[PDB]
Amino acid sequence: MREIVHLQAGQCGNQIGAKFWEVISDEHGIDPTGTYHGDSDLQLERINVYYNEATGGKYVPRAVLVDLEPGTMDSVRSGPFGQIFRPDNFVFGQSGAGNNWAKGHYTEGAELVDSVLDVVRKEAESCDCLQGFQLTHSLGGGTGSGMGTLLISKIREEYPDRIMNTFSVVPSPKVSDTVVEPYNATLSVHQLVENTDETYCIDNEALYDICFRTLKLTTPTYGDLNHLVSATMSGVTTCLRFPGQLNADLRKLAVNMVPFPRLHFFMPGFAPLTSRGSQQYRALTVPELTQQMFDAKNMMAACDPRHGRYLTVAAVFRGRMSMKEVDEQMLNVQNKNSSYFVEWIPNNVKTAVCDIPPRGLKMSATFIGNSTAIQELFKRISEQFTAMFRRKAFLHWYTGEGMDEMEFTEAESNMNDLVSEYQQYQD
Amino acid sequence: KLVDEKFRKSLNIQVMNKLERQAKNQVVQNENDEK
Amino acid sequence: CIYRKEYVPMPDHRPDFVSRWYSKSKMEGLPYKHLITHHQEPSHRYLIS
Amino acid sequence: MRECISIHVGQAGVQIGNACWELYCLEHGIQPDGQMPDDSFNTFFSETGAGKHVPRAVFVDLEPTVVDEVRTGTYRQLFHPEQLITGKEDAANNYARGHYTIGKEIVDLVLDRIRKLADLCTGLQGFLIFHSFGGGTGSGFASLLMERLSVDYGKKSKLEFAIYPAPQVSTAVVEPYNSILTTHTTLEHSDCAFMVDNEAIYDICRRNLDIERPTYTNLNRLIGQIVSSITASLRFDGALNVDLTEFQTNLVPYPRIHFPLATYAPVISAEKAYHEQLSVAEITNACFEPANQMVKCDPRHGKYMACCMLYRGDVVPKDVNAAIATIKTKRTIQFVDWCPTGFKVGINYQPPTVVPGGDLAKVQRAVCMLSNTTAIAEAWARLDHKFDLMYAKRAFVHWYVGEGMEEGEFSEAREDLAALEKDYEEVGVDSVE
Amino acid sequence: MRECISIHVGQAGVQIGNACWELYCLEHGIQPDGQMPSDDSFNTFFSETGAGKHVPRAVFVDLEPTVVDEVRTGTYRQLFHPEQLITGKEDAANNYARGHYTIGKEIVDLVLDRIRKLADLCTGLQGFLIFHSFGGGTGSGFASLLMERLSVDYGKKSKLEFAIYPAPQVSTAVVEPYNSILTTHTTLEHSDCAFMVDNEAIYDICRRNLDIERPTYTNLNRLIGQIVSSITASLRFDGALNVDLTEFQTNLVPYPRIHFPLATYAPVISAEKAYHEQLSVAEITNACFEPANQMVKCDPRHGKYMACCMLYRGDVVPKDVNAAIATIKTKRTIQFVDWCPTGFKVGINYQPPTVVPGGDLAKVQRAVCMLSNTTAIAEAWARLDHKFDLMYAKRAFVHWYVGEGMEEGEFSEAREDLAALEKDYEEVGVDS
Amino acid sequence: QNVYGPGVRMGNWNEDVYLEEERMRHFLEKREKGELLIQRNRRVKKNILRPMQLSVSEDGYVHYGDKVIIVNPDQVLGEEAGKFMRGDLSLCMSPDEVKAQLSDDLEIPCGVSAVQTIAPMGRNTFTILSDGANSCEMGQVVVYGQNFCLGIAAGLEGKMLYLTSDHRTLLKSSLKSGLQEVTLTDEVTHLNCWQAAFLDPQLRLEYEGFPVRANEKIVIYHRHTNRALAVHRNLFLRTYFGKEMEVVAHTYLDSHKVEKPKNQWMLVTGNPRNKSNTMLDISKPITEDTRALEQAMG
Ligand SMILES: Nc1nc2c(ncn2[C@@H]2O[C@H](COP(=O)(O)OP(=O)(O)OP(=O)(O)O)[C@@H](O)[C@H]2O)c(=O)[nH]1
Ligand SMILES: Nc1nc2c(ncn2[C@@H]2O[C@H](COP(=O)(O)OP(=O)(O)OP(=O)(O)O)[C@@H](O)[C@H]2O)c(=O)[nH]1
Ligand SMILES: Nc1nc2c(ncn2[C@@H]2O[C@H](COP(=O)(O)OP(=O)(O)O)[C@@H](O)[C@H]2O)c(=O)[nH]1
Ligand SMILES: [Mg+2]
Ligand SMILES: [Mg+2]
């Protein structure tokens, strides 16, 4: 019908994916064994979209889990939902990449992609009408930044037509856990722009903000940080899976979102976020949701949108609501903040509705934005990459893998040619 | 002549190298299972 | 003998097994119910088209 | 699966081996007879049919006595008698003896033993070599074995844990000669080093640990803690596991500059730690105070080049991030111009298990730092100084000459380290105009 | 059913007959009386009587009584039947000629009569096992005579041959090159295999592997019994790949004049060395290829293998046999002649080898045996030729042999027959 | 910088106290309802470890309907190498505890293992029932060569789990050994039958069709497969109860073609005096020895 194959690479992607496959496991009413224990028919009418039919009333993921280092996959197999992912969907090498993009993309990335290209091809012909592909990784590591993008270069040659969405994890400058990150980031962003329909720039600093100030969590670990990405995961496809007043899918937003193919770097958000103290004295209504999207505080990107102009903005509402308030609020926020939108596109705001709210909640929303201020992140990778390329520092880890230096030169050339044409559109 | 004879044997080593890798991967899979 | 006196066998010590368990669950963190569930709604509270 | 091999040479090698392997056995719960009554159990102790386990180390020495102590010691029944190797005559603080005449009789036997031990292993990760620059065996024999090991296994990682002679105190006179002579091998056939001096540990134990009359055993327990906390990421499961390849990648920016400094926190006794609350900021700044260095050099006289940062225990990424932020907002800690980002965070969960009868108290959270910085260069400058003022009158050269190595190679090594210090100054140079 | 008869010759043969037959009793469960305890694999070696006692199918022969009389007084005095152990009043005394022409024919008929009776009892006789030494006179002279006369009574029947080659440095005799050179003719035309072993090589093995700094002949005798057990083991006990004595002859002897393989046993390690070592089948085949563990003083790194017989035994999986043999092929200092692209033969046995009390090998789950035919054994014959011609030049010790009644022309011919044998071993070394 | 404990009312104390109340309330509701993991596991393990009393062999024989226990003795296994657990082992039903915490339902099929414990209890007590197809009435004498079955009730009242095994396929095998595997199922089939054989291979036909004694060494042979019940004393299995052995169905033979000590099996009947005890723990008479002085006289 319209099926998604969920790709999963790197340590980060392996974890948020297990986190992502926890929410859509919770909502669809399927127990950790593999059997459906929900209540309503609507929960199982479209489950072909993420789950594959298997004998005995049991469903299995359309998920491919890849990691060069086998250390992490034992943890995914040993979580609460570790009895759901097929072992043949696990494919692993023996040695990690050591946080080198070159190794994961050229030397040991070659021997594994044939395995990954095989199983996705098995899942390519398994369903009848695929809607697209969807991947999670990190540009700051060695495998997801590396072999994760190698698949992107390969699957785009195999299936040009299908939409490709990437929920990638962009490194933060104020908090850095890797010095060869501005290398691997420079060498993956270059690989993203030509072969990707829509990129969701996720970071970790802004997520550390959100729990601290919006949720007042005293010890926010990686697990709670993984909760919010999985929330935004289901909100993107909350319309494809269910009925509503105004349905949508991945393609309807994407064509409404990309005026020129070089601009597909986004800025995702999640609405109902308040403290554990305020679980009673806080009204769950349409306008207070809209008041929560368009702050710079709820945002899980590493940029302040007030420094740029929102090109296009999409709001996907979840749950049942009367419609008139949304067009009133989305129009209202357009009029008052008229200086923060580009004039050359009218009616900048996109609205879609599903009728079903998520589990344990009455109303939900997801906001995906293309704005100028995403340029502020890309200039400052080059602010770090130039400082490390000019002294040729840490370089010999890369030239030992057979690559040249010109790839480093042309990678900076392509990002420079991205922001330069990105800056003209703000002015 | 002699150069061709060396490459006649460096093609053979890959076969047993593949066999060794395959057996080691299977043992790795079982040692992951029990853990 | 220095070496013998230092490396006497000394039983009765057994390595810990549960501090790792505590740290695993600390890294796990709070579940869904204490994350986003609002007004303590049950499973079937809002499932109508 | 991931596996390390340890290559301990000399009296120092075998004694740090005693302490480290004892800590390993006690942590994993191995009985001293080699039996058991959530990871590893294959990196270090491979298991036989009868539930017994055998460590992946080789202890080599050219004198029998200290290894015969282990052969009669507590763990006599745990170590395979083939692995422990001995010779009649030692090198007697002479690189010439340790490298040219007596090393050859035994290097084939040692390489055969390590080749067997490799064939035991399925996926070998790398080699850790423990020695001293000041010993004849631990200098010359280790240099030969590294030279032959690099060509036997071209790709395998090779780490060095070396006892660098202290700036003032030492136990030998020709020790600068041996130190000079080992550096060419440790430069062109290595990947990373942990040169540590004994004086720094003496001061740190007299200062924090309140033992005014320590032992070499007390030194050895701390070095064992260092290596265990380093390999702990492979030994256990973790949020941010790091591999030897990973921290080689963020410890070597250039192939000729592979000389970090190791540091550990918290180092504190039971009575002292009964009061002071231990937290992430406290341990992360105690690891930054120059009084805690295990190398006698002041980082305030250099600029940090890269930092590898391994936490362990009840650690949270939030407070690691906050600690890094607090240490980054500081002027007294300087950085080279070309390194805007500077830290590797690795995390493990197993709280540090205490050796009873030792010195450290039971600690719930620990941290180690492996800092590539340019302040190690002045130590080599002083070594160069003493080497010149002993080479000027050709003192002590007749021993080497009569053993059979040429004199001009001494000047070769002098020129080598002169070039090395020149590269360190060149790296310290910054391009701000 | 299958049956094997031993024709052990000499003090080497008799003292081997003690050690090998001690193992056969313990593996089948025979008491030293002969009766099994109150609480039919054994048929190939023993034989049922009416009394239900199992009489061994061996014939100890010797030309002096002192060696055999110790068996008559030893622990197993009541196991061996009296007529089987043949003695004599005078011995050849380090002389091929005495044991072949003047003393041999005295007892030729008596043993050839006894061997027929043991052959009569056996319905289907698998073969003849002959154990002797090239050194001693009876071990060389008499052993050459019966092999010639065994051939005229049973033409088809195999005559497996295990001997003691003169060691290249240690020596318990002086004139032994005459005994070593002249006997080899019979081993050339009247033997079907060889298992030559040198005591010096075994002296190296025991001190290096078993930690016994001061061995004796028994320590050398025990390992030989472990060899003969393993080759026959595929006959006695069931396995995944049973291999007979006729089977391995085919895959080890490409030419009639080339029948000199080499033996090797692994693992041979003490309990304290079986303490701290995992024993996998890969760990015991790489040991069977190193020259230091070999049993002849020759190095196949100086030659080229032409055939190999792998004899596995114990808790083995045929999957991992294939893994081990594959890794051996990926090695350049293990060579093969160009006309042997496939140079292996594997037999598999289920029962692990037993452990005798008072021995040195600990009880082990698995074992490997090997019979490797290489052309690097030819260099062993060269030193014997080199020593023979230093001493035949001045006609030393010659007067003994003529005075015992043999013509001097055989000194030329026996020297020459090896010269053709060495040249034949160099043609195989050439690659077309 | 001065992070404080729970009750110090500090900083982010209000929200933490709210959250403590939330988690505490949730735990209280589950405790009141009875869904706690502690409670559930305690109840199910009690219903497993419940003790009982065995049957008494009046004539020294076994009958249909008698409660018994399956135990392999500790013969002198000088041949065993590696690590082998000694003592007398008892065949007892073994569940998967992971599936127990996942679902409260009974686990079909349910494994069988061996634990070095001869105390009668709910885990290891077998009723000897009839063939189903053949009318072997309760109280009749068990005979050599006659099919019989053993059953154990567990969990819900009325469960009659029977032990069975089937001819090996690629899709079913023992968990570690790889040989034919035996497990407990509720259904009734012809695969459920078991036969007993006399120890000595020589006189087995002579003792065919004869009454079977209790607490004596015999061999067990599944009818359809002809294989035998065997226990691998080397392979281990860690479970919640502890270290349990591996049991399979595969006949084992020595070089003299006799069953090796892993095919020996002993039934168990109750001690007539003390009910909690079995026959194998009955006391021995206390008397003194006269053979030393007797042989001294000669
Ligand atoms: N930290 C520490 N250093 C040690 C230890 N043992 C020896 N050393 C150092 O090693 C130096 C001397 O080298 P040795 O190991 O004793 O001698 P060697 O390496 O065997 O070489 P030869 O003297 O020729 O036999 C001393 O100055 C010590 O500083 C130890 O247990 N701990
Ligand atoms: N390896 C081994 N060699 C033995 C043994 N017994 C005797 N020999 C060898 O036998 C050689 C001497 O010949 P013997 O076997 O003793 O005597 P013989 O064969 O009866 O011939 P004569 O001495 O002439 O009577 C010595 O060189 C030994 O090497 C043994 O038990 N083991
Ligand atoms: N958002 C998020 N990031 C993570 C998580 N786990 C690890 N990371 C980040 O991933 C980065 C390291 O990625 P890495 O494992 O080396 O990627 P790989 O080399 O492709 O496998 C670190 O900077 C972490 O901050 C997680 O659960 N969530
Ligand atoms: Mg020394
Ligand atoms: Mg003799």
Image (cartoon, coloured by chain):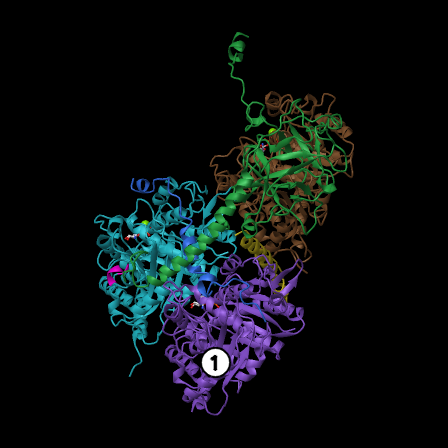
Chain colours: A purple, B yellow, C blue, D cyan, E brown, F green
Does residue A391 sit above or below F235 in this rendering? below
Residue F55 lies, in percent from the top left, at 62, 28
- How far across and how far down the image is residue A414, in percent? 47, 84
Q: Can residue D418 be seen?
A: no
Secondary structure at badge 1 equals: strand
In this orientation, which residue lies closer to the viewer: E17 or F9? F9
| Residue reaching furthest to the top | F297
Displayed quadrant of residue D321: bottom left
Q: Which residue is mark 1?
A: A369
Q: x, y (%) of residue F291?
A: 54, 12
User: Disc 1, ligand 3: is the CB inside 8 Å?
Assistant: no
Residue A289 location, x and y as percent?
A: 45, 75
Work out which quarter of the rendered image holds the C terminus of chain A and state it: bottom left
Q: Give the camera-side residue of D163 and A135.
A: A135
Q: Is residue B13 above or below residue D65?
A: below
Is residue A304 covered in magenta? Answer: no
Query: In the rendered view, does E78 fall on the left or right side of D332?
Result: right
For the image shown, how many numbered marks are present on the structure? 1
| Chain at tag 1 | A
In the visual, does D33 lie left or right of B1? left
Q: Residues within 10 Å of mark 1 (few under 14, many from 20)?
A: many
Residue A184 in the image: above or below residue F280: below
Q: Magenta residues, as a range?
A: D290-295
- D291 magenta-colored: yes
Closer to us: E192 or D221: D221
- The reply to whether residue A344 is in sight is yes
Q: Nearer the viewer, residue A393 or F268?
A: F268
Q: Quadrant of the rendered structure where residue E78 is?
A: top right
Q: Is residue F97 left or right of residue F173?
A: left
Inspect the image, locate mark 1, and give the three-letter code of the amino acid beneath it.
Gly
The quadrant of the rendering that contains the N terminus of chain A is bottom right
Quadrant of picture, ligand 5: top right
